[PDB]
Length: 299
Ligand SMILES: Nc1ncnc2c1ncn2[C@@H]1O[C@H](COP(=O)(O)OP(=O)(O)NP(=O)(O)O)[C@@H](O)[C@H]1O
Ligand SMILES: [K+]
Ligand SMILES: [K+]
Ligand SMILES: [K+]
Ligand SMILES: [Mg+2]
Ligand SMILES: [Mg+2]
Image (cartoon, rainbow, N blue to C red; front, side, top):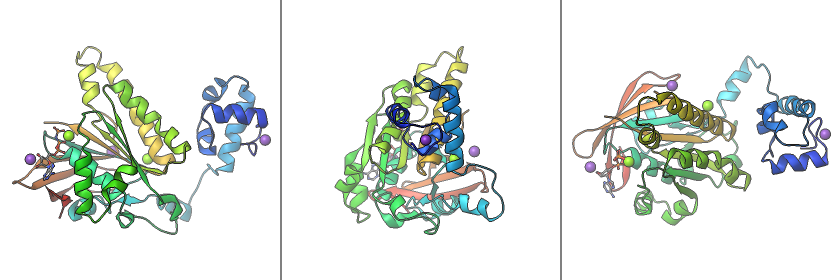
């Protein structure tokens, strides 16, 4: 931190204590955030932000450099061939993917399957020239369970059928039970803490994304506050995904809010499930057929 202009030893200490440890957070911070640190003037605040942006080369980029940025995105396999295809490879890091679906469509299954697949290194697709092994080494998952449907048994099961050690999945997945939107949001904001503590958080699951908000803001006479809070929650999620190059998944029970990728899942015949990609920034809408068995997502 003392590398930054306007940052002395005493200032560095305040910064690390206020949770500002890495350059990107400072580079992307506002003067307000930094001035609420006490002992930090605005001039010093503005100087370090400018410095952080420069040390992180956050300026205009063109030509080939535009390709390199996009190459830092790695993807997580879903164990479904058709789904990975419709996804253009698999679930993208640096983005928020949503699986909306009717009751029992498999939203929660996909979340569990994703935590398991994170532990199979061959399920993380990436350009080894833009993403080093170390960056995806000892990957960990954060599971914000708002429904109370996290099932370690399902994790163990999905894991064995994948030839992955179940306990290892459990040992590398942080679960937080949220009972309302307040807890749901705070847990997400605290993910930074797990990372500063040395945890290579690469997957974040929010199941469910909307249940709490709908339950608390029932009265459609204050839907504004609702949209606001949630919007702020999505901002936090998108930033988290970009800055920590990790995949963010969210579920939504349906039978408006921000989401980079949008799916609507429905039940087919028995095992069958039909997921429809109806919105994304660079891919055409498409359908993916797969099934949910004792092994998890397959085909
Ligand atoms: N151990 C298992 N073996 C085989 N199939 C399973 C197993 N566990 C769950 N399933 C399937 O997963 C379905 C439930 O998927 P689920 O992820 O709970 O849907 P959902 O969309 O999250 N439901 P909801 O949260 O209520 O809206 C079941 O009804 C089973 O068909
Ligand atoms: K300095
Ligand atoms: K079922
Ligand atoms: K979108
Ligand atoms: Mg993003
Ligand atoms: Mg569910």
